[PDB]
Length: 53
Length: 52
Ligand SMILES: *[C@@H]1O[C@H](CO)[C@@H](O)[C@H](O)[C@H]1NC(C)=O
Image (cartoon, rainbow over the protein chains, first blue to last red):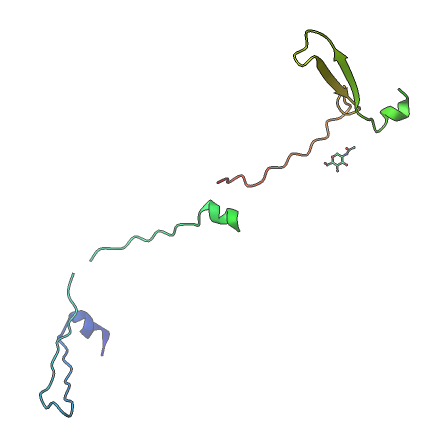
């Protein structure tokens, strides 16, 4: 499916009809809303790591 | 001492015994590179300045 349809959050259903049980199985999958910007820190290795070698 | 002995000088020691010494014996050592040396040949290396 296209991306903006998933970002919009429309409900999607899968129809499961297996042989022994004629009753279909229905489920709902949607993307919840709620956005904080991550802060990335890249820690250098400790000087003891440079000591061990 | 002979001059060739001072060249590539060996350790010459002055050992004196007296009542007033702490261990009753003291020692002083001189050679070419200690007593009034012409040059101070030293090699100074530092490694792992970062430390731990
Ligand atoms: C002076 O020191 C350097 C480096 O340690 C050494 O290569 C050289 O042989 C030394 N010379 C004398 C006369 O001790």
